[PDB]
Length: 129
Length: 108
Length: 49
Length: 35
Image (cartoon, rainbow over all chains, first blue to last red; front, side, top):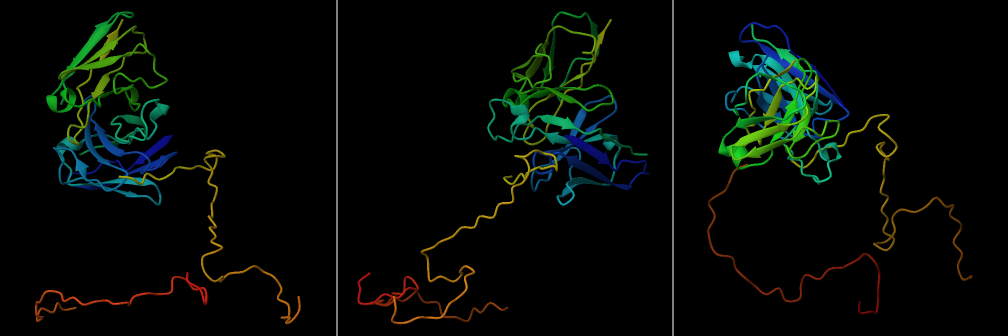
């Protein structure tokens, strides 16, 4: 399983970006596709998550700005970034939630809830400057 | 935001118990807590999904637990490579998941 | 959300590789026959076995 | 399209269907039989 990321870069205040996360070995449909930010030397404060279809679930502190979508044709989850603020400065991870039959665990049958995290990508640095 | 113990230093071999506080909304009532481990620069790897359950590729000495609004880690037999922050992810607390601050361990 | 599509690779594996299935489902006693096989048609013969 | 409202509002009426409404169950010929 591999996860490649792109989109982060140095921009002035109030700009726009487009985060691209392409998944090889699995899709944006197989397991929950989360977005996490890991501030340098702080915790990983959850941003958002796109499920296998149709979700607008966001965090309490970032409501009404982040928009989550996918191009299933190219298997890409997009996090379109508008109206930056100070606290969003972090390294961003597109997180693959533990898919069905997680590590062939001998108890869970098709329960896709499984709210933990599988292997991820290398992370993208998103800086507000 | 669950609170975790700060940076500490110690000896290999014995057991260290790190307990982390929480609220009754997520840890006290629901039981979908998972814990992770990361090396600075590389992405976090799974240590204990469900805490009691243990994924493969991980030494069996790692063990965690939850008690009321508190989650405890009973880690056993430290070694040199074990120096990495341990992160606690509980249930998504009515669809808004939360974590702990981080426990940076140090060895001699 | 119930969909959760497949995942394949060129070298995913023989089971993982996709057997394109066409379920040719036939009903032989449903109605007057409309589709038939490629057989040459002979002349019609009457009053003979 | 326009929604027409100038319609008298009465309850439904009822009648007797008698022996109507039977149709050919198939597209096959049968004769002098009860099937």
